[PDB]
RNA sequence: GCCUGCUUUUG
RNA sequence: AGUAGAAACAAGGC
């Protein structure tokens, strides 16, 4: 809450309130610099994102085999080992996998 | 190593260094001669982009006028002035549907304003084209000459003092056969200066009342080529005043406008609007921002669409209101244009030069001109009537910006998702000839479709977008009127750079303005403290060199380096002297908000303090409260604004001298009128002191009120006070003789 | 410069007529040494950026 | 080196006040310094200019 | 010899 | 010549 208005911070990806430039490595909050961010060598550059969904991983980009793009609020139907497609973020489709 | 500053942009972003991309330390481009060519270009352009319409001949002017309204639909992405009535009215209707009561309330406010306001409101403004002289004059001069000719002819309703009566007069003056005017001359062999009467038939008066003056705009930042601009007359001024009042009242109630707000209000509104959009937008939705300019914005926009808009906004109002707001778009649909100074010709063999006025381009052989100009004249010759070209199908630069913004917001309001009937939508921000659009959709196909629909819905109204100068990125970064938003607005500081020198008003005023822009730029821009100290130092160097006021403990020979040394040696306390009298500078960040006299008032010597600050000085001139501590300054990328400076009235608060060229011209007799009027008004302020603080009111001649107050003050001051009997009798005798002079 | 910055910031930039922009830049490069040098610098910037 | 040249009132006026250039540069420099001083809560002129 | 050195500059 | 650059200056007016 900021001046009675709900600023939304996006879990997956950048936002106008929270954006990390990948070029000059500066972090930016609300138009104000908040420090240069350093390169951990253990940064998994594998395309996988395990901290976006609750009980699901993100294996990569979409594939047309596993059907159309399910949505965030209709994922409890799935079960163990059931890969699927999900549209999230700024209109971006991805593949996911349950644990 | 070879040096490249642009490579700095490989580490620092372009918005956090955009000040480097503004070359505002050098002289700006200027025009040198005539502006006839650019006038012709604009006329033939706006007749080109509206050419498939239909031609007609006015019965009153005899002029060929091109009507493109409800013309064919465009077939390519070139500019078009083919506007459609039904879609304009649908835009207005949906606007009122989404923001109900907007037109009613705005009309009520403007009705109050219409009923109360006065003719004196026309005195304040910019210059004005005077049909009485066929050139530009100040606003009050034009008003006065127009009123004089009216009263000389018979129109006298403006004696009421209201504006709407002056408008009734200018309307009633069009239904007269032979208007009469008076013209200045002067002859010397003995300088004889007089006047002569002449007549103006009805059609002549109409073309003079409907025409605009044109001239080229100097000191433009950001363009390779020069532009032409227009200046309207005195008769189209009250009507457009009321129209822009209505448009202001409307645009104030719209979250999309940017025109009636300035400075930080503008940026605040923009930022609040962007946040509101990004909050109403969804998280699964893709979002993009177009940074956009419109091409040929002032040529496509037609007054007939403005008349449609007016008649829809005055729906269910009194007919006098509907009829006093309908006259501006009429008079700007039958308008004309003066071409200008003309051209100049050259002969190398005989070694001579010549000038050619614009009022012979219809009656001149085209051998002299080059190809481009020959083509121009060839196209324009049909439209010439008495040295002025017909121009119906478009506006000119700098007028109806508010109502044009209303139309822009009307188009932006067609992206509410209950008017698109789909899953994409849009909104944005609009100022005249600049905009920022924000488009939302679940994919890139919807983004393209929304962009296409915006383009087409805007082409149905005559709004063309510059593809050459527009670009689309994701949300977070954009540009709007030289404001660079990067997740927040950003400071530039080079727009404000020509404001850091001597302003050229007087010593006190230039000093105060110089320190005040430094502290302002410390607040608003991001000028640091050390750089501000340096700015002080450099400003004081420029101040001293311009005004020839060096420290006094120096050996710099100027024309007043002797008086200042005598003042230096007389004076005991030298930290109390002003920089203009040869003293030091005690300014720093701590005390930039204090004038130069209060800063050093305990340090002054009493004799200097009493000489400098003396009301009997002959150098000071205060006339009216609206001009006491207020100066016109001329920024980069804007019009001449007015700056308030805190200062104390001293002997350094002088006025500089005048141009003095008008002595050599036929219109020399305006000086004598000015001089006599100033004598009379000065004497009136002697009798009535409040005449410069509060506007007087009355119907009597000035002499009547003057002699009356003389008698009253004489009586009241003799009864209990200073006046004896001799003075009483003598001044009553003088009053009697004044009566014998006025009444006979 | 600003659309290139939008590309470096990974903001998916786009245009409607880029050759018009180039034709408008090139319309001003005529005969001044300082301006041609700035243009040369801009070409070097595009070469070292855009990578 | 001998030459004929020419100038105008406005060109003189604007070359009579070139000291403003000193501000432009310096302003940008201080901005950069301040942009780091906000990050590391300390003044950074000494680090930049010496180290 | 006399007079002049911005007499026409959008928002 | 030179300044400059889509039209002007290289003094003008009576």
Image: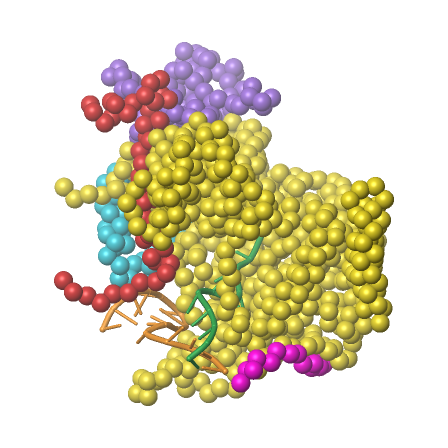
Chain colours: A purple, B yellow, C cyan, D red, E green, F orange
Left of B703 or right of it: where is B492?
left
Which residue is depicted at the point 25% across and 42% down?
A: B5
Q: Is residue A44 above or below residue B233?
A: above
Instruction: Judge from the rendering whether residue B132 lies leftward or rightward of residue B727; answer left or right.
Output: left
Q: Position of residue A96 (x, y in %)?
A: 41, 20
Q: Nearer the viewer, residue B690 or B409?
A: B690
- B181 left or right, relative to B369: right
Between D12 and D35, the residue placed more toward the observer is D12
The x, y position of residue B73, in whole percent, is 58, 62
Q: Quadrant of the N terminus of chain B?
A: top left
Q: Is residue B388 above or below residue B458?
A: below
User: Which of the 4 quarters of the picture holds residue B708?
Assistant: bottom right
> How many circles with numbers are drawn on the protein?
0
Instruction: Report which quarter residue B173 is drawn in.
Output: bottom right
The correct choice, above or below, for D15 with respect to B274 in the image is below
Q: Nearer the viewer, residue B306 or B442?
A: B306
Looking at the rendering, the stretch of residues picked out in magenta corresponds to B188-203
**Can you give x and y, in whole percent of width and height, for residue B541 in the image?**
35, 43
Residue B741 located within the stretch drawn in magenta: no
At horizontal 49% and vertical 31% (from top left) the residue drawn is: B601
- Verify whether residue B201 appears in magenta: yes
Quadrant location, the C terminus of chain B = bottom right
In this rendered view, identify the residue nearer to me: B286 or B719: B719
In the image, what residue occupies the spot 84% across and 68% down? B740
* Residue B92 image point, x, y percent: 69, 49
Residue occupying image coordinates x 41% and y 84%: B368
The answer to whether any part of residue B332 appears in the image is no
Left or right side of B310 for A26: left
Residue B463 seen from this side: yes
């Amino acid at each position: 809450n900021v001046r009675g208005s709900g600023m939304r911070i996006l879990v997956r990806g950048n936002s106008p309130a929270f954006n990390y430039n990948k070029t000059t490595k500066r972090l930016t909050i609300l138009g104000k610099d908040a420090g240069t961010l350093i390169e951990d060598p253990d940064e998994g550059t594998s395309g996988v994102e395990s901290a976006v969904l609750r009980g699901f991983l993100i294996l990569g980009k979409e594939d047309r085999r596993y059907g159309p793009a399910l949505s965030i609020n209709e994922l409890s139907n799935l079960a163990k080992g059931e890969k699927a497609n999900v549209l999230i973020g700024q209109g971006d489709v991805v593949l996911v996998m349950k644990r | 190593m070879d040096v490249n500053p642009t490579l700095l942009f490989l580490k620092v972003p372009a918005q956090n260094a955009i000040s480097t991309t503004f070359p505002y330390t050098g002289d700006p481009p200027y025009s040198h001669g005539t502006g006839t060519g650019y006038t012709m270009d604009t006329v033939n352009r706006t007749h080109q982009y509206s050419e498939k319409g239909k031609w007609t001949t006015n019965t009153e002017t005899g002029a060929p006028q091109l009507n493109p309204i409800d013309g064919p639909l465009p077939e390519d992405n070139e500019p078009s002035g083919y506007a459609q009535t039904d879609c304009v009215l649908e835009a207005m209707a949906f606007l009122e549907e989404s923001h109900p009561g907007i037109f009613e309330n705005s009309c009520l406010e403007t009705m109050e304003v219409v009923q109360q306001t006065r003719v004196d409101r026309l005195t304040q403004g910019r210059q004005t084209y005077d049909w009485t002289l066929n050139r530009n004059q100040p606003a009050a001069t034009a008003l006065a000459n127009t009123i004089e000719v009216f009263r000389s002819n018979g129109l006298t309703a403006n004696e009421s003092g209201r504006l709407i009566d002056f408008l009734k007069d200018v309307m009633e003056s069009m239904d007269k056969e032979e208007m009469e005017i008076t013209t200045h001359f002067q002859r010397k062999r003995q300088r004889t200066i007089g006047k002569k009467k002449q007549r103006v038939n009805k059609r002549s008066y109409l073309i003079r009342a409907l025409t605009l003056n044109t001239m080229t705009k100097d000191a433009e930042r950001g363009k390779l080529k020069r532009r032409a601009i227009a200046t309207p007359g005195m008769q189209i001024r009250g009507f457009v005043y009321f129209v822009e009042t209505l448009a202001r009242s409307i645009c104030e109630k719209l979250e999309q406008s940017g025109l009636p707000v300035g400075g930080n209000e503008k940026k605040a509104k923009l930022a609040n609007v962007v946040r509101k959009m990004m909050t109403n937008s969804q998280d699964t939705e893709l979002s993009f921002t177009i940074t956009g300019d419109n091409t040929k914005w002032n040529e496509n926009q037609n007054p007939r669409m403005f008349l449609a808009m007016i008649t829809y906004i005055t729906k269910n109002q009194p007919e006098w209101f509907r009829n006093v707001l309908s006259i501006a778009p009429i008079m700007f649909s039958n308008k004309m244009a003066r071409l200008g100074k003309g051209y100049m010709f050259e002969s190398k063999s005989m070694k001579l030069r010549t000038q050619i006025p614009a009022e012979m381009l219809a009656s001149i052989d085209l051998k002299y001109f080059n190809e481009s100009t020959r083509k121009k004249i060839e196209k324009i010759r049909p439209l010439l009537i008495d040295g002025t070209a017909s121009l119906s199908p478009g506006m000119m630069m700098g007028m109806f910006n508010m109502l044009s913004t209303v139309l822009g917001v009307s188009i932006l309001n067609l992206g509410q998702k209950r008017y698109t009937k789909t899953t994409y939508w849009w909104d944005g921000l609009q100022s005249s000839d600049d905009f920022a659009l924000i488009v939302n959709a679940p994919n890139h196909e919807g983004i393209q479709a929304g962009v296409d629909r915006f383009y087409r819905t805007c082409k149905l109204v005559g709004i063309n977008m510059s593809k050459k100068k527009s670009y689309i990125n994701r949300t977070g970064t954009f540009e709007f009127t030289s404001f660079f938003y990067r997740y927040g607005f950003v400071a530039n500081f080079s727009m404000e750079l020509p404001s850091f020198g001597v302003s050229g008003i007087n010593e006190s005023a230039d000093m105060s303005i110089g320190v005040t822009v430094i502290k302002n730029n410390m607040i608003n821009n991001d000028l640091g403290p050390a750089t501000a100290q340096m700015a002080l130092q450099l400003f004081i160097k420029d101040y001293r060199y311009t005004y020839r006021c060096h420290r006094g403990d120096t050996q710099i020979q100027t024309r007043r380096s002797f008086e200042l040394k005598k003042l230096w040696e007389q004076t005991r306390s030298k930290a109390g002297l002003l920089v203009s009298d040869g003293g030091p500078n005690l300014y720093n960040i701590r005390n930039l908000h204090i004038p130069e006299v209060c800063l050093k008032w305990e340090l002054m010597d009493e004799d200097y303090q009493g000489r400098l600050c003396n009301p009997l000085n002959p150098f000071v001139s205060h006339k009216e409260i609206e001009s006491v501590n207020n100066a016109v300054v001329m920024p980069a990328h804007g019009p001449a604004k007015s700056m308030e400076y805190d200062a104390v009235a001293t002997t350094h608060s002088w006025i500089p001298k005048r141009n003095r060229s008008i002595l050599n011209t036929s219109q020399r007799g305006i000086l004598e009128d000015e001089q006599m009027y100033q004598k009379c008004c000065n004497l009136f302020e002697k009798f009535f002191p409040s005449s410069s603080y509060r506007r007087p009111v009355g119907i009597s001649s000035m002499v009547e009120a003057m002699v009356s107050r003389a008698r009253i003050d004489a009586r009241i001051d003799f009864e209990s006070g200073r006046i004896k009997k001799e003075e009483f009798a003598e001044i009553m005798k003088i009053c009697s003789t004044i009566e014998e002079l006025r009444r006979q | 410069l600003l659309v290139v910055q939008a590309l470096r910031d990974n903001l998916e930039p786009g245009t409607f007529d880029l050759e018009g922009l180039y034709e408008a830049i090139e319309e001003c490069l005529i005969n001044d040494p300082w301006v041609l040098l700035n243009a040369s610098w801009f070409n070097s910037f595009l070469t070292h950026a855009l990578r | 080196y001998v030459r004929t040249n020419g100038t105008s009132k406005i060109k003189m006026k604007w070359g009579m006040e070139m000291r403003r250039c000193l501000l432009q540069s310096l302003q940008q420099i201080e901005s950069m310094i301040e942009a780091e001083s906000s990050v590391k809560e300390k003044d950074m002129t000494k680090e930049f200019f010496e180290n």
